[PDB]
Amino acid sequence: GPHMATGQDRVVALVDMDCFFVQVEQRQNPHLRNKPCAVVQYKSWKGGGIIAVSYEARAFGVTRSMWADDAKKLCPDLLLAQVRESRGKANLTKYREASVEVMEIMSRFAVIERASIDEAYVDLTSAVQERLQKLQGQPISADLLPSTYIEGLPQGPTVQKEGMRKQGLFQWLDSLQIDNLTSPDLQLTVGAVIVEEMRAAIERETGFQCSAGISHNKVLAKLACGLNKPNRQTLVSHGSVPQLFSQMPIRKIRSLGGKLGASVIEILGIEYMGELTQFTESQLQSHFGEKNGSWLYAMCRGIEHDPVKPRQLPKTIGCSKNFPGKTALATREQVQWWLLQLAQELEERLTKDRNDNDRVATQLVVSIRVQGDKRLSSLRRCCALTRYDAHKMSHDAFTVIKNCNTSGIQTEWSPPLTMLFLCATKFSAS
DNA sequence: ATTATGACGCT
DNA sequence: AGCGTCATA
Ligand SMILES: [Ca+2]
Ligand SMILES: [Mg+2]
Ligand SMILES: [Mg+2]
Image (cartoon, rainbow, N blue to C red; front, side, top):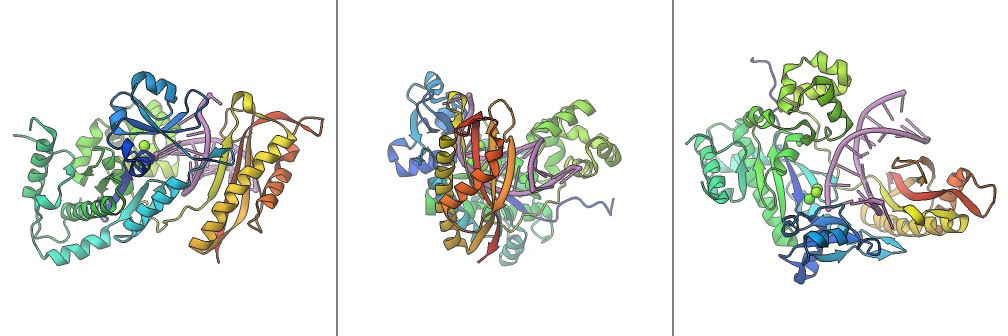
């Protein structure tokens, strides 16, 4: 009772750009704004692979991973923007730079952990205390929360969505105890006020819209964020957890979307996150290991302790290309030419990295896939990375993988390579 | 013939 | 170290 920690110690947000690559392209080309549109890479094979989709286009059933030709069957007027190509491969620089724009804005408000090219966790705990002292027991106006949903509300005794949103928000605010600087619900609420401000600043200064989740930890924040998209934010309180989890498929929780989540369902014979509460910590540990077992026991109760790491910059810089089906590399000349193209992009990105961020990578990781293997990577090998020179890097990469060539002939390569990957890692200050 | 990434766990 | 898992545009 009095000694059970409830995982209400922090306020954590997760900010996620809406259809991010699409917005980057729409900002640049106003003709694409407010239309069904998608971003595609390459174009010759089935019109190109779709990697991002506007909300207008999703309404027609267009999705990521769909071939553009097939998307056009669902959405004939679908508009397309193509990822830039350089050195014969997709080049994602425009999106990486747009991401930096957003991350630098977020960093003005609080410490952020860059979770992906378009999302960051924010630890608001400190910022909330501060704001709480400026407010001095002042109630929080619904006006300060114009895009916020309160998960689980309204309840009890509204035909249209904005009306529901507001009814829910009013119930929440009318119940709030602002007299108490340590109420976790109040802290979450102040968190949401800050996130409205952050989101306003991002949109003002970049033109990009985003959604966000505000809760007591990263898993709940991430889940919350997806509840109302696009261009909205969702507060998931500790109290909302039991109802929310009672019908929440296990696979929806971050880290449970793959094989572990599949085994939780299979081994325990359950479907929903809430059903986990009926097992002891020991039981969960026996099936899923000490760490996972402990994590699951706490998580199904809405509790998680993973910190927002103070890290705004990626830890690795990598360049990758697939060579699918008939394009698999089958000669030594080919392999060396593409290792060079990858190495040239990598050098360019590394040099800029060193200038902007005062660090140097020290390890080069080389990875390939061979025709047949259904794994992302067939083989990984690292070497020293002593100079930012593409010719040297490609030469070193060739050296570490060349023994993979089955071909008895020097000039031929077998089995053919269907993927090449160069990654710079292990940065040190400079 | 989704592709191009990126973080982190296990042994 | 090299491999696997899980994630996102
Ligand atoms: Ca997004
Ligand atoms: Mg995202
Ligand atoms: Mg997405």
